[PDB]
Structures are given as structure tokens and as C-alpha cells.
Length: 128
Ligand SMILES: O=C1[C@@H]2CCC[C@H]([C@@H](CO)CN1Cc1ccccn1)N2S(=O)(=O)c1cc(Cl)cc(Cl)c1
Image 1 (cartoon, helix red, strand yellow):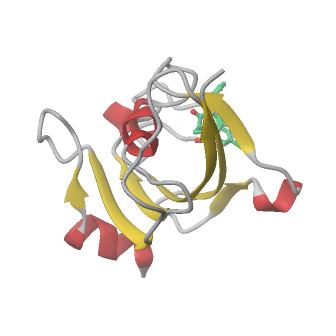
Image 2 (image 1 turned 45 degrees about the vertical axis):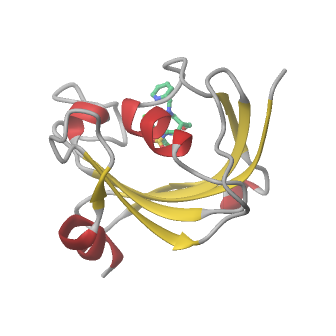
């Protein structure tokens, strides 16, 4: 399925080239611009664990997830991955635990040493 495909065929987008964050662009976005550090970004997403279970979805809340990029408000894989996205892009992101919740996990939903899969749509980004 999609998690296997990003694992096997995704691009390593880490600066360290440690295959900790892998990406496939699923829907090509607009032009060339990507958000910059500190921008307010609006996304829709769904996340899955490696046992196949969906653990979260913004779509199901009927409102986007909003954060300021590059500030550690989200897991490292998201600061790295969303920074690569164009407006309107949809991507798949595979996040090894070192770029997510590590050995601690995040109870109740995220176990220890969890590789996470996301589908992310970048709706908008704006400077404040
Ligand atoms: O960094 C995150 C990432 C990436 C952005 C989208 C979500 C948000 C909103 O739930 C949570 N965070 C930040 C965060 C804040 C507080 C505790 C743990 N993580 N998550 S997430 O991995 O989907 C997530 C979803 C759910 Cl339901 C619980 C947890 Cl612990 C994590």
C-alpha cells in the first residue's frame, strides 16, 4: 500500500541523508514557492501507525491543522517535510521515530519507536 511505497520508493529529504524522513509528492502543487520559517501554515492530514491503524485525521474534524513552520511546534519530520511543499501539494511522508516521538512515544496513541505515515495537503501559508 501507500506506506510500503513511500518506504521503498520515497525521496530522503533529510539534510543528514539518514533516511529518517521519506517523501512522495502525490498531487503537484502551484509554482515553485514553499513556505518559509515562521510562516503560519494550514494543512489537512491523516496519520497511520505501522500496525495499519489510522490514528488521526484533520478532515474528520472539518477544519485544518495550523502551526508556525520551523519552530518545533510539531515533530521534526513535519517541520522538515512541510517546508518542502508547494501550495496545493499533497504528499506522503514516512517519519522514523528519531524524527517523530522516539522511544518515549506519546501516550495514549503513539507507541514507543513508532514509524509514522502521513498524507498531508498544504492548503495555504502566510507570513504574519
Ligand atoms: O507534532 C504533532 C504531530 C504532527 C502534526 C499533527 C499532529 C498534532 C496535533 O495532534 C500533534 N503534534 C504536536 C504535538 C503536541 C503535543 C503533544 C504531541 N504532539 N501530530 S500527530 O502525529 O498527527 C498526533 C496526533 C494525535 Cl491524535 C496525537 C499525537 Cl501525540 C500526535
